[PDB]
Length: 358
Image (cartoon, rainbow, N blue to C red; front, top):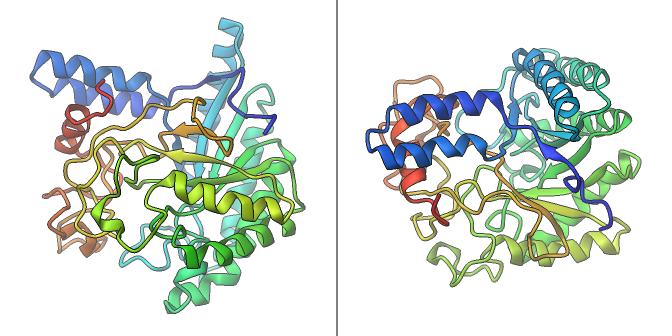
């Protein structure tokens, strides 16, 4: 549409990922690969607000972005992920979420949103783009036979509504997570998904700040595949462009001129998975297409890097209380540390296998 949130702005580079990358590049012994690895700190990524403890860091990032803007005569944009629903990740074998529905989860979530709003309100000269709750509403399309998801449905809906309504009041541009081609892109799932997302958009008042949907977050699908990955057999929507081209008209029909952002941070290497559902530290992944608003599609505002490559998806240690056995599959790089922590060997491969090359 006419308003692409990225046009005319400089993206603030995450200081946390820059620090991880600088530390990682020192440990790469080949001096040429080390230089390529170091350059990754200049590629914009999203910062994940996956616990209340990260909210003060957001305040520092907004203040630093505001000052950099004044120093350089630019307008700065900060990219964040809201990721703290109660009973988070209801269909997963393990969740690291700190809030539970049974212990005042919704009230704690609303307080988490209120604290984020209070930070954003203080720096109106900084634009914020937010991805809203990966691995949330997509479960309400396909995973309602998982008891934890059925029990979380009304809380997930109420919490997402609280986030959308309140972040809109401070002018945050929002993209709700919408899974990926191998989750919601199956033709039979498109209409239920369109119905759910349109309902959520309506309940939140149809705010123009609810821009659309984010796809492929923390996943590995191609935007535009040369030929279908074998794991996709049976689904005509074998890449993200097919999924978006099929879903976008259904949202438009309901009155929502929705646009999309697509994660390509770990999409450089295709045909590396044994099954489409394998998501944990997939071995051989490379950095994909760098963030850009030159997307080639009327429906896609930007290619983005949402999941920061190198931060682990989950541990392979079966003694961990956070263990998810998906992280033990053969196509998963092992041994792997705890989710969120730096996985140096995996980063080194992301750099080496980058396509396009770094």
